[PDB]
Image (cartoon, rainbow, N blue to C red):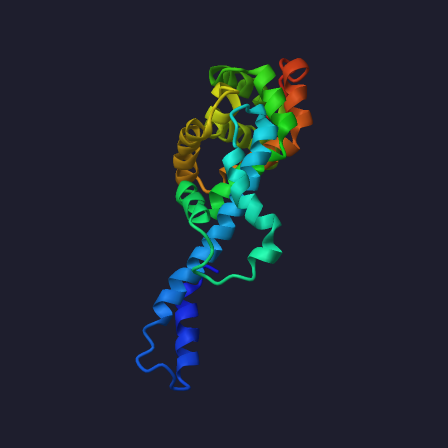
Length: 225
C-alpha cells in the first residue's frame, strides 16, 4: 500500500522466471490493486464520516455511504470474486470520496471522538470572533512554561482551522454541503500538517480551557512581573 513502484519492481522480479513474454500486463494489475486499496480507504473514510455525524450532531441522511459498509460487512462472500468483477457501485463510491486522503481521514478522526470539546466550544464562543477574547484570558493562565503557553496557540489554531464544522454547520447539512465545509478544512490542513494533532491536544486539556472562563480571567500570573 502506497508503495506501488515497489509493487511494480516486485512483479518484474516475478516475471524474471520468463513467463508471458514482454510482461506489460502487470501494469493493469497494478492499477487494479490500487483500486482495491483505495476502495478500502474509502470504506474507512465512510465510518469516520458517520462518527463525525454523531460527534457534531448532523441530520442530513448519509445512507448511501452504507453501500461501502455493505461491502465491508459481507467481506467474506464478496471476497470470492476477482479484481474486476467487484461492481460499479463501489467504483461510484470511490468517485465520491476521491478527494480524501489518509491525512484528511485522520483530521476527521481527531474531530469525531471529541464531542465534549465540540459542545463546550459551541456553548462558550459560538462565534470565532469571541475566540480572540478567550485567548487573552488563556494567556494569563498558562504559567510562562513553554507547553503551558503553547496550549493557547494550539487551541487558537485548532479552532481557527476547524471553524466551519464546529460553529456554523447547519444540522441539516447534506452530503455535498458537508463536502464543501470540508473543502475549507481541506485547504487548512494543506496549509498546516499538525492541525489534527493540535485539535486533539486542545481537547485533551479541556479542563484548563473550562477553567479559563471563570477563574484565570484576572489574577494575572506574576512570574516576570
